[PDB]
Image (cartoon, rainbow over all chains, first blue to last red; front, side):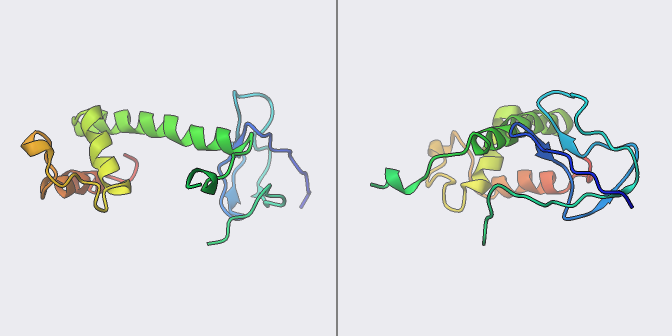
Amino acid sequence: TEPKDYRVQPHMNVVVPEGARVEAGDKIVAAIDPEEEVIAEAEGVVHLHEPASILVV
Amino acid sequence: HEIGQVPLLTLEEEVELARKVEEGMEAIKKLSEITGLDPDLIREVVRAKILGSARVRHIPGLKETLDPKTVEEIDQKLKSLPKEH
């Protein structure tokens, strides 16, 4: 396994569950417009590791 | 003072909240495209749940509007869609 951290922009949004399955022909984080920012290269798991805030309910 | 109860939004929260609505507005069409029901109507029957715990007006516009047993049947058709719609 090989780690690699992508930086999610303010004007962006993720479409991945709490560490779920990720394919090679998939898009993880949606952007303002499709920039060469987030396209999946290889199989693995995306881990959320810095929310800007936390909601407790 | 009621007004001070609600707090300001982030340059990210503002954005993120807005993105839900535009899609919701599209979704509303997308539904009316499939159901064959009207955008103006779906938008009511959807609001008549998110707000309509009681919000379903006391008298339905003196029967201009319909708020009785009718609401569910619509949201019952919307619940009874195949998963992708």
